[PDB]
Image 1 (cartoon, rainbow over the protein chains, first blue to last red):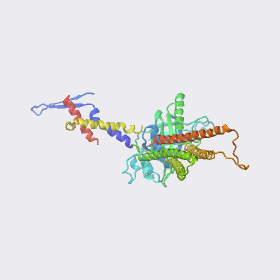
Image 2 (cartoon, rainbow over the protein chains, first blue to last red; image 1 turned 135 degrees about the horizontal axis):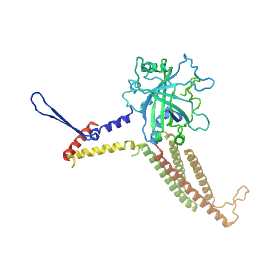
Image 3 (cartoon, one colour; image 1 turned 180 degrees about the horizontal axis):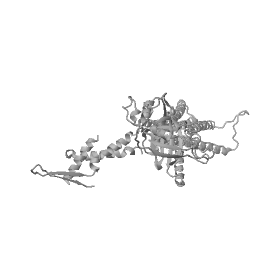
Image 4 (cartoon, chains in turn cyan, purple, blue, brown; image 1 turned 45 degrees about the horizontal axis):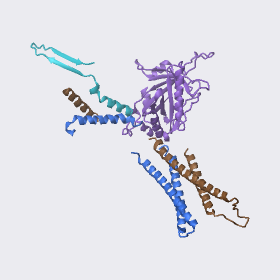
Length: 47
Length: 253
Length: 108
Length: 109
């Protein structure tokens, strides 16, 4: 509604990529026969 | 339920801009736009409430207020999207006409609120009023609608109006409001606060028994009033004007 | 810098006290000339009228202009804020510095 | 307030005019006047007290002129001080900027 609150919200949201918690994901696909391919997904977080 | 301690006043639109600047010089905050829509409901006269204890006057019938916020997309006409959404738009709101008409409000049909006449006695420096409040979050059923709900309780619609203005937040929980009020009917829309702004400064107290807090609140309100001496005169309104019981009809506007 | 209106206001005020100083100086010369006029030489008699007239006209219009200024005070009524944006501008400049840090070709 | 200053400057100006006329008449007829007619009113009875009253006039006009001028100057400065004091008056680029900064630090750390 008011300009000031939206301006502050925009400026604060601009820093999300720095302030937010880092995350990582690693997907490992192992080559197996008999159309049986297990998957190994490891996600690393720092809560 | 709160004890609201309030002071009132009015100003002509000519000084409006100037007034705004002075407020920002004191509070250190910028104004924030807001709007609202209030509907007043009264007990149904078709039903005879013999339960009013006439020989004892345990209670008297009263009026219920239902309030809701309405987005500005209903209040801005085709000539006004160019300007940004800030307080200056109020400078164009001097005509008795307004984009929101009767049909849209009828299509709409929240916060439920009841109040009492202020405390008696002539040794009161600020208007002290008691308010009982609740909130309606949602509903369901075959007739889920505000009108059907209030008819289920036993109340019927009386009138409605629209407030548009600005808000200032100061220290100690003090809130200062500049308002413009538009009454709405099928016949049309009429601005009761014609050529001016209604000013209201108030604080809320959660518990009426605490008296140290009430004394502090009164001290803050009187200090604020004594700060604005010479520019605007803030006064205690008439105790008989803020009475909203059905038996006697008048409306401070 | 201040808005211009204040600038010509202060210029007019400065003109006011300079005119007052000129009035005092002319009072000094008229007091000087009256002495020798009482002494008894009539050569500087014509200068006396001019000095008196200029002294009075300097005394009058200065007060008139000051009256105009005080009148301007009457209608000029009604006609930390920087902090509200101060952090913002600080923010801006800091990121600018980062840009200068981020580009190694501009650090020369 | 300002109206009081207006009035004060008014007696300031009229006092200047009156004391100016007084010192003018005193110095012009400082040469004592002797007229046989009863209409004239100029008395010099005690010889040296005449000079005392003369230096009286001198000291009065000096003090009053200096005080009035100084008061006017102080008034002007006060007006100027009141004038000075009382008159109350992209985001995406930042996103890639911070992304490059953080990746550069991560590489360099």
